[PDB]
Image (cartoon, rainbow, N blue to C red; front, side, top):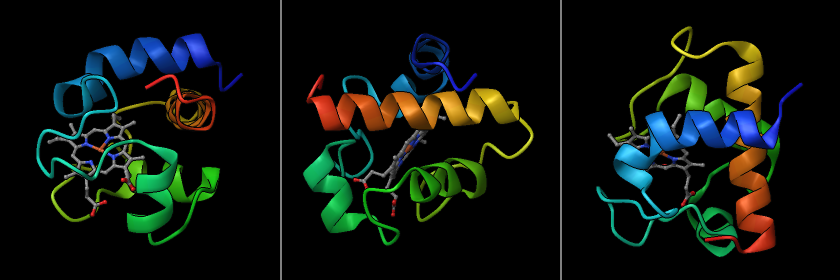
Length: 89
Ligand code: HEM
């Protein structure tokens, strides 16, 4: 169901590794923030754009293609989007 709690559970395990509290450890300022997305993200503040990054891996970010399920992928994207939009970073 591309759930946010699912998305969180994924995030917490998989993404937090580099992005702890939306907190990009590799490129300090390239955080999971709305603003940071809208500047740095190529594809803009769009679910498509988010998902695409997570799938395919981009710059210094690993690809999650087939490592996460489709729903899982969608959930983590949705969650990140919700966090950003809501400012729950
Ligand atoms: C876990 C599956 C995971 C998610 C979710 C995630 C999201 C994410 C987004 C949405 C961006 C864009 C942020 C912005 O535009 O400012 C992004 C960017 C980077 N990530 Fe990430 N990310 C997840 C996992 C990981 C892992 C495990 C690493 C660390 C090895 C990592 C690193 C990075 C880096 C670097 C970037 C910037 C690269 C770029 O977009 O050019 N991510 N991530």
